[PDB]
Image (cartoon, grey):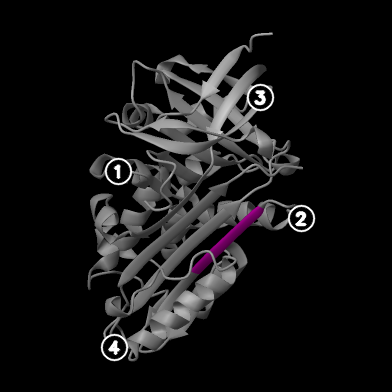
Amino acid sequence: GPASTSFGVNVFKQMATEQSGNLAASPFSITILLAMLQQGAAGNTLDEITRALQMTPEKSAEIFKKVNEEIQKRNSRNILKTANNVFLSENFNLNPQFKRIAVNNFDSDLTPTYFGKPALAAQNINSWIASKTNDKIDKLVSPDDLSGNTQMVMVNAVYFKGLWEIPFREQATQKRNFTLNGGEKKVASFMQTRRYFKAGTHKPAMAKVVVLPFEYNEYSLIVVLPLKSSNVDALLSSLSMEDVASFLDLPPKDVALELPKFSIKADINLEPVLNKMGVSSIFTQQAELYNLGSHGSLSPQVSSALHSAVLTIDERGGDEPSLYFRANKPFLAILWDNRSSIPLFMARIMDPTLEHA
């Protein structure tokens, strides 16, 4: 259900309280990072991770094996590209069992890496990420973050560009004003259609909801728009993923929809937020990750934990309305996996004209 990615949703919500502006992240990728680390953890580190995930190592491995299986079964024009890896310094011997679980359950790997030439290491990691993400994510790792003393670089990146079940008519896309928080007006490209969508008003959230399906209903874009009486950060704080899951049961309504085109990219260093979310041990020299790799009796620790998320929407697809849904002010967008019932992407869209978070 949505409980499996609760840690990642909590991380996203924490990050939202600390900065304004566009914000995008994958609860799936952030949870995969921790659930993968759990498979090599012991002692206090294992305890911290288990408490944060609310899953045992055996449970998280089983859940994400199936989530990944359902993704890889898809043969459609929806493009979901993931890049998960653990780059372990060659000063450490990799644990073959951890590597097996990485590959067989987490769509990830354990990869020996020489960090003594930092520019070469950074570019090799970035080139691998770019090769896995249709070249959409290509500069996540900086050479200045690496040195001969780097022990472990964790990367979890995700790119999504889907095809709507029904297209937006390109000649219906129109330039209209989008009003930012605070009052600044900016021209944006609003895609427009009028169709039946699962939609409604969530009063516990003081917000309108529309569910926009992608091809073969593999995914949905769930768009949540605060009413005049509220704002997007109040909305985000109160909105549970159990609420979001229920939106897929909303009856179809005749909706006149105006939705800005956007493409949002975020590159995120997770160490600050993970230090706030109860898993600080993984970065310390007291980290207990000996079943991930070993140097004599020494455990590695996490040197860098890096996440990138890219989500792009456009028009392409395969007598007064019941609801007007005009997203010409800040709103929330959630990319939902309809088969596994988890949020793959969360975005707070403050300004659809800007591509960065």
Provide the residue designation for mark 1.
Answer: 14
> Where in the figure is residue 292, as x and y percent of width and height?
42, 74
Residue 26 numbered mark, or none: none
> Where in the figure is residue 347, as x and y percent of width and height?
44, 42
Magenta stretch secondary structure, dominant: strand
Name the N-terminal-most of marks 2 and 4.
2
Q: Determine the secondary structure under disc 3.
A: strand
Could you tell whether 59 is left or right of 65 in the image?
left
Distance CA(mark 2)–CA(mark 3): 24 Å
Distance CA(mark 4)–CA(mark 1): 32 Å
Q: Quadrant of the N terminus?
A: top right
Residue type for callout 4: Gly
Provide the residue designation for mark 3.
Answer: 197
Residue type for callout 3: Phe
Provide the residue designation for mark 4.
Answer: 148
Name the N-terminal-most of marks 1 and 3.
1
Answer few, some or many: residues within 10 Å of disc 2's Cα (few below 14, many 20 plus, some between 14 and 19): few
Residue type for callout 1: Gln
Q: Determine the secondary structure under disc 1.
A: helix
Q: Which span is picked out in magenta?
A: 79-84
Q: Residue at x 45, y 26 (%)?
A: 225
Q: Is residue 26 above or below residue 167?
A: below
